[PDB]
Length: 283
Image (cartoon, rainbow, N blue to C red; front, side, top):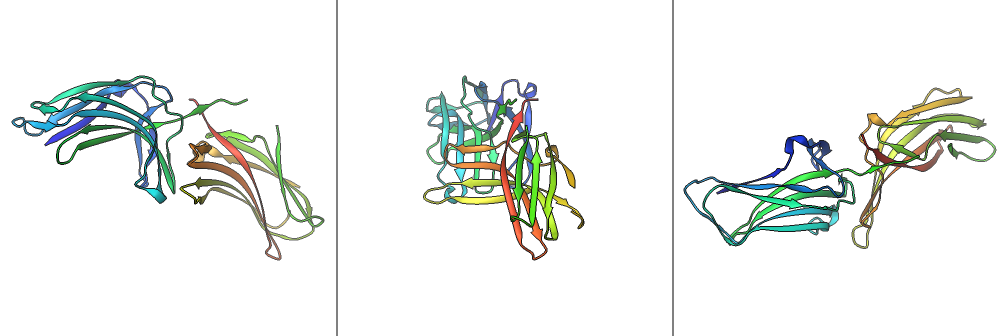
């Protein structure tokens, strides 16, 4: 019947960004920042040159929403712009409709998680008696930040095991290098195994319940039994990372931790973790 296309102005002049979809594929989408105008045209193409198409209105929407997987039908839209493009009538010929949303709120970064998703899109809808012809084009949003000593964390019993991990920042951008050192200051118990992890914690809070998903992004092992310091360098740019996302519209958080892990000879596990705020540096 109809083929609806959504075409952005300055299409081939604007930046695209890679973003992983719920499946696992990484597609490229038009990248927008907070505030930016979103404009273009909704293109209608009559499959049958020779045939009207009746409708109860054509409209374009800019929507920003949070979708919780434990409540999948119930979208939480945080920004909705609606611009009606046509009154009910009929299309008797392929044609396009201009649209512009000036000043578009996009407070949060796009996120495709484990129990939750935050996406922006344009939706063009042709209302009809039977079923609406609906067309959605996702667009991706990024949030840039700008920022400016030593941070320490330690693990193990009292007299018999004291390990100290020291690193340069409490904040890192997504291409940064975590520069630190492991100090073995006391080792009366044999150490069977030790590692530094970077962990992504996704916290989704849907209804009375909160769900929690830990994802180990990077696992850096500390070798062979002769524990002196050992310098640590974790290269963030090698990993799939997103900025820290704190309490996004009180629906979910994505936070990152350095997780110090120590397994002794009696097989006792010693854990310590500390939050590092990730952020996106503007290119």
